[PDB]
Length: 6
Length: 96
Image (cartoon, rainbow over all chains, first blue to last red; front, side, top):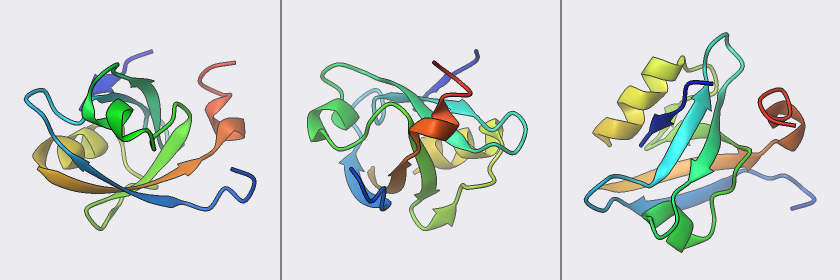
């Protein structure tokens, strides 16, 4: 699943 | 964490951000912590956990955020004030 670094 | 009260967590970004990944906001289901980078700010603070739902960031309600809205808020935030809440049951739709 797409995940986004922050 | 038997009460599952939301927690206010203050993080200060390093050179590569807060040091966690978000997942969710694909279909109104909310924004969750998928990954916490070893030796990044979120890890070193000790407070954030995998399966936390992100409820707000610097006073902005992310409960109903899309992935993209949440990314925008979190990326544009120095000292960032996060409200997080442990929601393992909801997170189980992402990861068993």
